[PDB]
Image (tube, coloured by chain):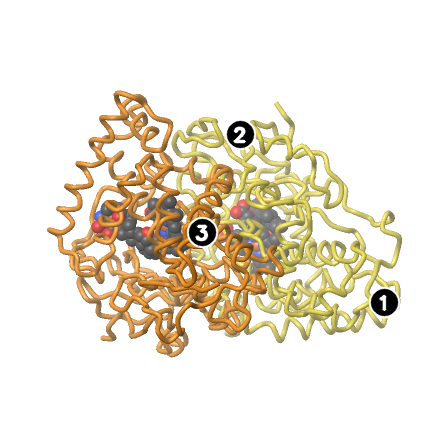
Chain colours: A orange, B yellow
Amino acid sequence: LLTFPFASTGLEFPPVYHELYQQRLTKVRLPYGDDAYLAIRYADVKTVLSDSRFSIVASLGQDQPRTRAGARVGNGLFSLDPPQHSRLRSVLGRDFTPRRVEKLRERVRELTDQCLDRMEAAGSPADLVAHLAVPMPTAVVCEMMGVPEPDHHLFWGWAETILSNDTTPDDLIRRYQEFTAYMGAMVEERRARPTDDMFGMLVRACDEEGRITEIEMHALASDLLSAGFVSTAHQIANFTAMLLARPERLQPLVDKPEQIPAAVEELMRHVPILSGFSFPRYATEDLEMSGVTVRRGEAVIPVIAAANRDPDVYPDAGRLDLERNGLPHLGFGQGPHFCIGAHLARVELQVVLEALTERFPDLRFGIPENALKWKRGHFMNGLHELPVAW
Amino acid sequence: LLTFPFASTGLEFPPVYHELYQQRLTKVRLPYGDDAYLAIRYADVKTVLSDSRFSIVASLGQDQPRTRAGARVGNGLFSLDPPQHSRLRSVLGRDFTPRRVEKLRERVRELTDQCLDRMEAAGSPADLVAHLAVPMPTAVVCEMMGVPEPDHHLFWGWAETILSNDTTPDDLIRRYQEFTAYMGAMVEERRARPTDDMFGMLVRACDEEGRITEIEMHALASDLLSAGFVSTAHQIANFTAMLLARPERLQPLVDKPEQIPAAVEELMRHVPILSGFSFPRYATEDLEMSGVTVRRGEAVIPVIAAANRDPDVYPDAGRLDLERNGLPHLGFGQGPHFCIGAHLARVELQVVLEALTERFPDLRFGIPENALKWKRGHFMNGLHELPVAW
Ligand code: HEM
Ligand code: HEM
Ligand SMILES: CC[C@H]1[C@H]2[C@H](C[C@H]1C)[C@H]1C[C@H]3/C=C/C(O)=C4/C(=O)N[C@@H](CCCNC(=O)/C=C\C[C@@H]3[C@H]1[C@@H]1O[C@@H]12)C4=O
Ligand SMILES: CC[C@H]1[C@H]2[C@H](C[C@H]1C)[C@H]1C[C@H]3/C=C/C(O)=C4/C(=O)N[C@@H](CCCNC(=O)/C=C\C[C@@H]3[C@H]1[C@@H]1O[C@@H]12)C4=O
């Protein structure tokens, strides 16, 4: 069988996908776990993500297809199907609706401004990863949750552990133990002095209203503080690097600031954020997909980066066209597990581009593009550093 | 209770939504059937359409909230929840993927050109509704299914019965009898001799593969010949009118054809196609929506038109901006029942704007704007006629 993931470096999209688009659904071998099919057509990835005949739960003795040594297991949102998944997420739902997140726009800009004050002070050329991509989205969720600045580094360490392909089940226990200890102390603080932040809301959801158990309270906290900043950090960097590699760099968005939202969406579509893949889903019954009968219990991987370059949905898919305004990309997923933070990410990315265009309109690479240190072996594509000059 | 639908005329967005968006989920009373909540925020209409806790089936004795006198009931796709819905739909799925539908672009343009030849031959001013909006999408699906041209008028009549608010269960009996008779004949004919058309595919699905039963084959065919062209017909005229009512008319799209797909999407967002509403959904368990506890069994109506002008999703929502390339609209719906024809409709609307810009760049209203005969009190908004000049 073909082995997956395929060879690529940086944000490269590998040419093998252009072969597979026109073939039937193909089975691949993965680094750990059972084999799986590769959903790469737009409609197929949509199906895998959103159709009730695909379960995110391995209930028929499957060995989870994956790139990480330890199978991804827990009691939080990625471990549940609807309706259980739906009631649990609805504990967070109302804090991530556009109507709520839109109110954060100002604070996001403020934090972004502080970061850039600090970058400007450091002087050209500076590492935009260290000065902006890491700090800003981390502050955003940590102050949303109620985690003090000085502990941010702990949550980076736990999130890298989740995301590292070389993490073992032991490594995950160690994480679980450390994280539980941390939040447990935070729970006790909030019980004695209640706070208005999200963790406070979670503690009340548990203690007062009896809406969730302690296990669910911790699980949701773990999900947000794990999923909630490392992805945006990687994208802040990926997005700027994509833009600076263009002859005109930021100038189109300097000239036409009203096109920044569209630009954010095109980049969401075009950047292959993952060198791995997310959760496989499993057929709850036999079903047909791209010329193949997928049997009950068999795993299908949703390759969202291939979806976002489907030749039939997106003409000239490999071209970054910031005016494309393409059909709706799958970069935040689809169906039940559609990114609960999708609007917050869009706000964070719109705000980063606003602030860079307004403050550093002549922003450019601070080293030769050829010297950029892309992450090589990692679950997520991105940059170790992004030196920029102004 | 607040009565719904709200007063509006033509494609006017009624101002009352600007009130309701700020407020908690509100309950309305309908022309027929039980009362229901009005889902109007983006995220809420999404939930209603996509969340498994919302069923399209009244399984607890409910009287379907509606504007039509006779309740909407049958054996096709709008009468099913997943997975039963999913299994029936999958019989058609393959034929409506973008990969399949993109192959129809040539033929859709051919038919659009024939329509425009007749219009031009009729002479300025001419009615674009009669010459293009009605014939072209009717011909597209009927020839897809294998229905001959001379019989198109019959399918228009059956479709309007379904869509007319003044239709009784008796009128629906007549329709069903007439329609079943007609497709029965088509079935005999396809059984006596194979044809490579969509109805012929349904016949193979019933007779040869035993995938579906005879009344499901009929249902599916009825769904497609009912939903499959009156909507596109109404939008072709709605879209053209929207464009012709602006100072610049068609010139922005003449000048930049590459923006035609984006305009189609903005129009889909902006145009309130329904005066009424689609199917209500029923909560299958207690849940929270916009500050209200929706109890099990209670109905919630997804108001697509309102979601598409959600003030927090869409800044300045009332403005038709063809470059907006906004966050994805709910105009083709969402979840299980997301329009099976969405790509075909995008193809049809794109091709119509391509053909109109290329052939009639100085297209303009053929009568004074205030004379336009907008449909009054009908289920869908639109024009009885659209005189155009060139
Ligand atoms: C550019 C940044 C981001 C990207 C590209 C992204 C992408 C995604 C994708 C594709 C999924 C679904 C994976 C699957 O279905 O297998 C997901 C889920 C999730 N994301 Fe995001 N995300 C981003 C930012 C955020 C933010 C800012 C937050 C929270 C503050 C967040 C929290 C979550 C959570 C909790 C889930 C699981 C939701 C569920 O299973 O119900 N993400 N994200
Ligand atoms: C501008 C044109 C169109 C618009 C605005 C439109 C809109 C919609 C919407 C919003 C729904 C879902 C309603 C709900 O969930 O309550 C739907 C369903 C449906 N549409 Fe379309 N549609 C269009 C064109 C078409 C075309 C061209 C076809 C051709 C086959 C078609 C066939 C269907 C069918 C069969 C369903 C039911 C699907 C299901 O329940 O699984 N429609 N449409
Ligand atoms: C750029 C977007 C990427 C996403 C990525 C998929 C990509 C599209 C998911 C993959 C999740 C793995 C999760 C995971 O391995 C586990 C696990 O081992 N146990 C549980 C409970 C442990 C605590 N919760 C979590 O850590 C929950 C989410 C963290 C990540 C999350 C990242 O945001 C980035 C679980 O969810
Ligand atoms: C602008 C788009 C509009 C859509 C509209 C909702 C809007 C968003 C739906 C509403 C459906 C009503 C359906 C309906 O009344 C019935 C009924 O009475 N019996 C069944 C079986 C009868 C045979 N199937 C059908 O007629 C199936 C679809 C036709 C319409 C369909 C039109 O595309 C237009 C049924 O579905």
Q: Position of residue A314 (x, y in %)?
A: 51, 68
Residue at 64% in and 69% down: B258
Under mark 1, the amino acid is Trp
**Residue occupying the point 39% across, 71% down:** A367
Label whose residue precedes the other's in the sequence (1 or 2): 2
Q: Residues within 10 Å of mark 3 (few under 14, many from 20)?
A: many
Q: Report if residue B48 is visible in the image.
A: yes
Q: Quadrant of the C terminus of chain B?
A: bottom right
**Amino acid on which the number 3 mark rests in the picture:** Leu
| Residue A47 place in picture, x, y as percent | 39, 58
Crowd around label 2: few <14 · some 14–19 · many ≥20 (10 Å)? many
Q: Choose mark 1 or mark 3, whichever is in front.
A: 3
- The quarter of the picture where the N terminus of chain B appears is top right
Pointers 2 and 3 within a single chain: no
Q: Chain of mark 3?
A: A
Question: Residue A195 location in percent, x, y?
Answer: 34, 26
Q: Determine which residue is flagged by label 2.
A: B25
Q: Label 2 marks which chain's residue?
A: B
Is B140 above or below relative to B232? Answer: below
Q: Secondary structure at mark 3?
A: helix
Residue holding disc 1: B390
CA separation, marks 1 and 3? 55 Å
B340 sits to left or right of B274: left
Q: Which mark is residue A105?
A: none
| Pointer 3 residue | A116
